Image (cartoon, coloured by chain):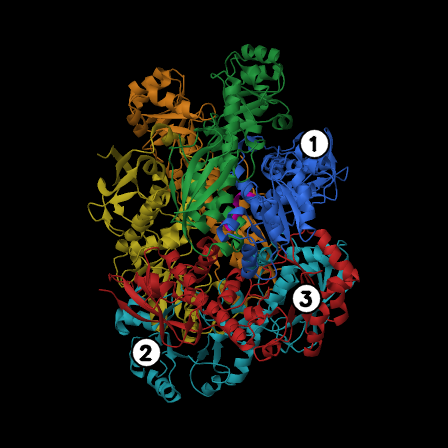
Chain colours: A green, B blue, C red, D cyan, E orange, F yellow
Amino acid sequence: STDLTPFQIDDTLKAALREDVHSEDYSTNAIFDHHGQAKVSLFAKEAGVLAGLTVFQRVFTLFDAEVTFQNPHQFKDGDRLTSGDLVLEIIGSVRSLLTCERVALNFLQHLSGIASMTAAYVEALGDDRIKVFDTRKTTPNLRLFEKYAVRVGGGYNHRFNLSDAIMLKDNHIAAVGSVQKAIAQARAYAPFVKMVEVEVESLAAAEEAAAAGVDIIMLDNMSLEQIEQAITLIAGRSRIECSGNIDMTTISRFRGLAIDYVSSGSLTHSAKSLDFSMKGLTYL
Amino acid sequence: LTPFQIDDTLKAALREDVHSEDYSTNAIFDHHGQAKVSLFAKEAGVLAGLTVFQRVFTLFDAEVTFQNPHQFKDGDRLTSGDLVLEIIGSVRSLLTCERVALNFLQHLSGIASMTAAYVEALGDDRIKVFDTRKTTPNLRLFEKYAVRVGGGYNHRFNLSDAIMLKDNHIAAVGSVQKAIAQARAYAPFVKMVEVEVESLAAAEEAAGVDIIMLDNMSLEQIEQAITLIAGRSRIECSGNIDMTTISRFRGLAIDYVSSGSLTHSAKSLDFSMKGLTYLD
Amino acid sequence: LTPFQIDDTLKAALREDVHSEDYSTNAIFDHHGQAKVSLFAKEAGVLAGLTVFQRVFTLFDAEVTFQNPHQFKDGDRLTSGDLVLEIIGSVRSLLTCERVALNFLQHLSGIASMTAAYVEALGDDRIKVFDTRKTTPNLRLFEKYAVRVGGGYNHRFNLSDAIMLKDNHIAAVGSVQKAIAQARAYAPFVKMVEVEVESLAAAEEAAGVDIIMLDNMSLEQIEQAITLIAGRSRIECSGNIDMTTISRFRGLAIDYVSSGSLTHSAKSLDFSMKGLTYLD
Amino acid sequence: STDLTPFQIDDTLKAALREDVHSEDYSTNAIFDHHGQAKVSLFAKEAGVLAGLTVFQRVFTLFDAEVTFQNPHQFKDGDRLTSGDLVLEIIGSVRSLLTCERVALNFLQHLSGIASMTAAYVEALGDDRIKVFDTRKTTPNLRLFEKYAVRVGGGYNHRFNLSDAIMLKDNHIAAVGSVQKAIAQARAYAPFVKMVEVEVESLAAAEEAAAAGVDIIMLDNMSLEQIEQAITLIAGRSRIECSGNIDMTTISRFRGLAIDYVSSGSLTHSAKSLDFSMKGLTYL
Amino acid sequence: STDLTPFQIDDTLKAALREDVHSEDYSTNAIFDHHGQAKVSLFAKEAGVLAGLTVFQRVFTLFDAEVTFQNPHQFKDGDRLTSGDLVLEIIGSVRSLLTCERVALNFLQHLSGIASMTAAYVEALGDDRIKVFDTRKTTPNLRLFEKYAVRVGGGYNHRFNLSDAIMLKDNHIAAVGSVQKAIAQARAYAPFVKMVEVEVESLAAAEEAAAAGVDIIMLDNMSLEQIEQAITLIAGRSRIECSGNIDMTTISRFRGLAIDYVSSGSLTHSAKSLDFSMKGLTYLD
Amino acid sequence: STDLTPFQIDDTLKAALREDVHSEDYSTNAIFDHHGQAKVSLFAKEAGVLAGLTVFQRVFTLFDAEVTFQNPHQFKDGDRLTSGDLVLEIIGSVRSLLTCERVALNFLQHLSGIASMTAAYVEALGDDRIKVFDTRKTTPNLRLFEKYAVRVGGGYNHRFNLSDAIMLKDNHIAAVGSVQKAIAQARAYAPFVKMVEVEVESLAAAEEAAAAGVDIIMLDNMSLEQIEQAITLIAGRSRIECSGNIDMTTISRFRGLAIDYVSSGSLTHSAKSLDFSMKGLTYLD
């Protein structure tokens, strides 16, 4: 239930406005010399989950401080939507509303998309002892936001960057040759403060990895027969994570296993964005 | 894309992914020589932002280099199992900024691929496929390049490029004839003027505007409005456009259709970096 | 000008002028209250970038405030001895960023003033006075605003705004008819197309291009070329333009003349900050 | 005889290129698909002094590293120009030449203007025991460059910013009330490492300022009768500087006085920029 | 351990050079032409440990790319120094050497200080099953560097920032009331990717914390009699860390215990910087 | 002296917060809601001098504008401390207090350290006609702050960077050969706006330097017998500065001389940081 501070996001939005408005909004400024106060209604035009509503609002307030917001239904991020819902009313100068509308929508649409998609996976999974995590597969320079959308949607967050945890991918192991040797080497480097996860595409190597006592074992694209085998072979010495080919329709196979979490890329990188609609402009 | 254009974006993306150091990688640093890694396309589609992929590595580590055995270039078509690039340099330099590069390459090659699908699905090649300002924020420059690569074309980059008069704008002045005159007054002869129009009657009242946009009109109406415009302006179609739908416009004397989804709703393409080995 | 547009420029200008601290000022810091300072115009001309002047102070110190007794606004005319602004706040906050603010105000009000002189000197007000990309670097945004303020209008902001085809470009394709077709091919219907032309013959071959620029042609020739264009395109004049000269164009059916000097060769206006006193 | 390092200026030019080329040079890229190597000649189209030639060159090399430069006459900054002089030849890709030409010229024109103007003042002054300084009256975010142009032109540089020296303007004195008290207060704050200059519009206050032993006294807009009086009244306890209403035609009045330097704003803020010409493009 | 990449440090060094050289080096540029080239010797003037030598070199190369470096004794970071030692020779333009010398020496001095001090604690501790960690008590905007110096000096690194691990101080526990409940609540919030450390000032609470299976237990300023009790009471279910009142002279009391690591502030925040100097300027050929 | 403006410091502090909080404060956010508000007391835990209190406060306000500050004892920078002293009370959202506490304490500790150490040297010197200056030996990208701490502590400031004054070291003189010629050449290059200091390791050269009328003469590591000779030999034509081997215990030898100022590195580069702490968290009303 944790929003984003302005300090975190203010620098990013400001660039998004400068992006969309190099010199001035000619189309808007030509027609509305008035700076006349108006109200505009933000409608959801699709079913899903709301995310980054505060971000939507912050875009307007950064362009024009004197802009204000009625919220009749007390809608908040994480609340579910349906077509034809009045999420927000936006009041202020006509130019201030018509100019930074596109930029705000772009964030709202994009984030609410990720959240919605996460929620679909979570409900589609069904098992709620098993959790749905995300990745660093993200659209660049927006990781902060995209990870918030996943939280909002029912998901959880994996390490934020390379400095958070020690995750040993298949390259890393190939480079030291051994797994036992790779892990020992990681643990040497950062002794007690860093979690150590290992990617593993064979039952044999998962044994060897659990032996050297790693924190998380990631079963990369293994079969259902093999996952079950590997859980009892690990024998709970480490956490289990599943991954690969985890789409909307696949995820349900994990229901009922004693894995701890599945994780997915698509949530962040392949998310259809939700639709919202800007209409009902009227003076006030 | 020039480096000057993109450098400052990529540098922030690296600082994003590497706040302190790459513990996972640095823990395995050895005394070994340079290594080679192979970039494989793991999905069918179009390649875009390969130079961007390369620039990410060179910004982290200047001493990194690139073999390209098949002379793959942006816009070239891909299929699963294709060796696009080989990447040679220090092992930490490869394993660290691999993710950030893949994120750009995946994301851009996705857009390009999707554009190309719409272009081939449309079929008519007198009719062109344009994009929009519906884009993921602070990456507009890149996303528009991907659309070019994919066979598409670019609409105005921002609000300051052209004058586009939406339905709100017209409602506010009341008239269309008066709204356009008022736009043309405000800016000098240098700005294009496009007008959104949801009725045959109002499309007549427009045409000399530069572009007329038929917003979500029917096939019967579009065919009527083209002859009613009588080529005094450009015709654009929009709305209710999806991969399946786009094919209706095939054979009309419109100039271009345009779409959002290309930029905002693009499944990203898949690549991968497998095949790490030390050089001798 | 919005603060978002300008903030990052001004902040660098302050860091420029104040690398360590204002020793001269800080050495005299007291326990006194807020002071008031009066901004006087010390020369005749046009006021421009007053908001910019104010933003400089507020970026250094948010708690600074501004009385404006005569309701002076940008574009208003000045004369020597005029009280434009009074500035109230901490004494260090006033004395430190005074120079940086004056530099913007002086510089912008100069351009605006000079524009206004050309506009009044031209006399014909069917004919408009445009500017160029000849500008002092990294201040183009501001300098173009000053030209608007001064009665002028703005040409394309950069190379990506419009397609302007100079004499080199035409020489390179050989033909004009072919050069234009080739430009219009490259970009979509959204880019204006201007053509530079130093002969009556080549101006005929142009007009449908959007703007035709008569580069340094004679009065006899301009009058011939207007009727030869026959209003199929816009006419612009350029070259050999100075305050004294501009008056020849008075009465022609050209659409606009354009000039460099407005931006690059503008004597800056004079202001001053006298009349510091402590408030009670 | 000191140029500008790339490290000093590279960050500023890069912004100037991004300014002039938001997306691409459509006009150039439409016509020259060839990337065909060409040569272009930089001609001076006006008499004056050359400044920031290295800056001109750096603009090209930042856009395109593979660009090169023939200089047939060994022209350098500070060298005098005349109309119809071949300063530089510029060789490289056709797009690379036609695109960043404008940006480079803008610097070259602007700097060579300042230098030229400085040189005019210096020669017009005639006395070469007396020096011609500049100010912080500068076009913003280009102070570094403009001060270099003044050096090139025969002039010298006054404090770069507020942190260099302690200069007490008439406001500052008005704020402490006394001059004797203002100076003592400055000297207290920064004891031995900072020069202390004082602006003075009366003979009486110049006495008082020289008494309290300041490093420089600035005679702000005083008459010739008064300057002469004040020099012997100072009695060489401090340096003398003159200022105000120092234009092209005025400056000559100071010739033969025992002041140390005059100083001027206009050099930086009111400098007509020199003209250069780009022509003679041909393939190679 | 391993060096620092240029990409990590470049931006920091560039600001440090802009800091020291706002307009130009008048003192240097007045006396020396751009044409001449010279060699300068970096001497260590004090006994200690070398750290951030690559950083020293990167400062020169950022100012002037054409600068180069002879290293006759193959000195590297972590190597021990003594007074008079020729660490580096530095060759290039005279201005390029005399100008950015101070800025480089500042980094080298500062880092080599931390490393040296760490090494003193490590040797003073004596037990090498017990490790010496550092903290976030650091001089600001140089945490990256200071933590590298600690590695070089024989030490190890604690969490880099608040986002690395979950460390539950005494406030945090007071706020939930229970420890068992506080930990459960942390583990709930960040489920599997975050280590969980707990500060504990009583034997009783260390029992309850080890029960709920936390990753690290921090014995905050406990007595030697109590630490020895608490280790067997934890019974190795979790890691033990000691802290508080750990200076140069105290640290030796922990020698021989079955704690895993002690940790200290002073290493980063209260480190006398080592001395070097750049003498022996002469023109080449 | 005077405080630091926000405009001067804001950018530095903002990076220090981004440094310490890359993602979020998990430890804090897990245990405490955004709604609750509390008071926390800043206690000095050590004897010394207070410096950069405004900086401490600016760190909190940059994270969270709605944070506020009671100061019961009207403590200001330059005021003396002793253990147990209630310097500040800090009121606002619980997260806002617990998160940016470390970053603020780091600045306060570090600066108050320098100030304290300066003050020790000043009192240890005893002569108050003689002043204690600092140097560019500083921890990088914090020179602005460290120089303010020296002011606060009773000291004064030397040139900020290479562009401030012209200081001619022994290399510079060796390079022109003469001193009389070196100085003339400096004065030629930057004519009237730059102070000129000269380093001198021999009585003979101090004569020649005072002759050519330089602003400051620096007696580099000279003996007490020699300093006393050189002062009368300069005959007050220029300022005298002493330097080298000036530590806590040495400095007292200069007491009673007619030098103008001694100067030291250690003040900035080798300063033990003062201790504070933030204890006494409780919820308001």
Q: Are marks 2 and 1 on the same chain?
A: no
Q: Is residue E20 left or right of residue C220?
A: left
Residue under numbered circle 3 = C231
Chain assignment, label 3: C
Question: How many other residues sit within 10 Å of disc 2, few (<14), some (14-19) or many (≥20)?
Answer: many
Instruction: Find the magenta span and give its range.
Output: E6-13
Q: Are marks 2 and 1 in contact (CB under 8 Å)?
A: no
Q: Amino acid at mark 2?
A: Ala
| Kind of element beneath mark 1 | strand
> Badge 1 sits on which subunit?
B
Q: Quadrant of residue F224?
A: bottom left
Relative to the observer, which residue lies in front, C81 or E271?
C81
Residue B40, labelled with which disc?
Answer: 1
Residue B123 is left or right of residue A48, and the answer is right
Q: Residue furthest front?
A: B201
Residue beneath the point at 27% across and 51% down:
F77
Mark pair 2, 1: CA separation: 79 Å
Q: Quadrant of the C terminus of chain F?
A: top left
Name the spot of residue A33 as percent of width and height, x first.
46, 57
Point 51% across, 56% down: residue: A30
Residue E231 sits inside the magenta stretch? no
Q: Residue furthest left?
A: F73
Disc 3 to disc 2, C-alpha distance:
73 Å
Quadrant hosting residue C45? bottom left
Comparing marks 3 and 1, which lies closer to the viewer? 3
